[PDB]
Every structure is written in structure tokens, then in C-alpha cells.
Length: 153
Ligand code: HEM
Image (cartoon, rainbow, N blue to C red; front, side, top):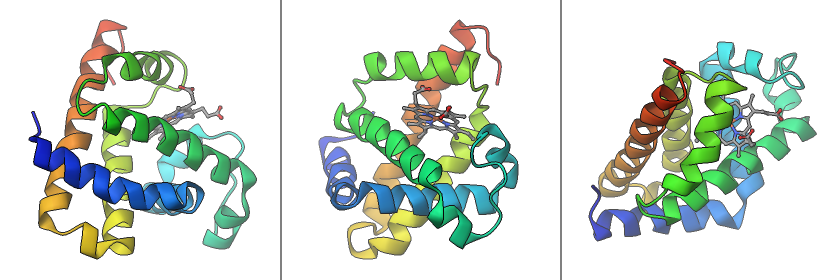
């Protein structure tokens, strides 16, 4: 359970993401696809992308980064009270997309990397630790829902 201070550090850096959701989403998905190319196989409209310029020119990738960050922002703003936001996400990710917990770890590392690269002043060790806790709680709760749905990914 994060402290109120930790949630405030999470939501403070998140306000910087909200100034340009699409550009942050592109940098996060590009980092995930470049660091873990096996993840790109889950995206039918983007699986052919090779270079960073191709990834930045992709309308599908730019739209999907916004899809992901819109959902994650709503989850972070619930400050751990996110059962109703996690329920539909666990449903699709366990039964349709089949996204293993290791892939959620990969995208978490990509989020932390981009926030540290773009906003180092608002992402020092205090804020990095608070965001790490917030993404770890997200993964823990989604893993338990995955198992409830019969998915052991
Ligand atoms: C922070 C973690 C993530 C969040 C908040 C997130 C959120 C979403 C949301 C809101 C959607 C659209 C609604 C739905 O189908 O549930 C979606 C679709 C999808 N997500 Fe995720 N996702 C996350 C992580 C991942 C990861 C790591 C992968 C793959 C490596 C993934 C693969 C997919 C795919 C394949 C679709 C369908 C895309 C399409 O057909 O256009 N997601 N995700």
C-alpha cells in the first residue's frame, strides 16, 4: 500500500505525461518494441515495423500509445482502488490478447525509462520508487485476476 505522499509523486509526474499523451505513448511503445521485439508480434498492424522513424510515422502505434496511457492514467488516479478499472483489462489481456505478466514487466520498465529520460527533475529516486510501487501493485492485482480467469501467463 503506497502512502499519500507516494501517490502524489506518481500523479505529479503523470501530469507531465498528460501534457502530451501521444508523444509519451510513442516513446514508451518504441522503447518496449526495441528492448523486447517479441512484444511487437502481438500487434497485427505494427508487427512489420523495424525502424524508430517507421514507428514514429505509424498512426496505429500513436493511437495505441494513447489507448494504453489513458487506461493507465485512470488506474493511477484511483490510488490503488482500481478493481473496477482492472476488471475489463484483465479480461481482454488474459483471454483475447494473451499478454504474459513478463510483458507487463517489460512495459513497466519502458514507462519508468521514458519518465526518467523526459522528466528527471520530477522523477528522482522518490518518484521512481513511488511509480515502481504503483506499477508493481497494478501487476500484482492483474496477475491474481488472470488466474481467476484461468490464465497462468
Ligand atoms: C500498462 C499496461 C497496459 C495497459 C494499461 C493496456 C491497455 C489496453 C487497452 C485499454 C486496450 C484496448 C481495450 C482492450 O482490448 O482491453 C488494449 C489493447 C491491446 N493491448 Fe494492452 N495494455 C497494457 C499492456 C499491454 C502489453 C504489454 C501488450 C503486449 C505486449 C498489450 C497488448 C494489447 C493488444 C494486442 C491489444 C489489442 C490492440 C488492437 O487490437 O488494436 N497490452 N490494452
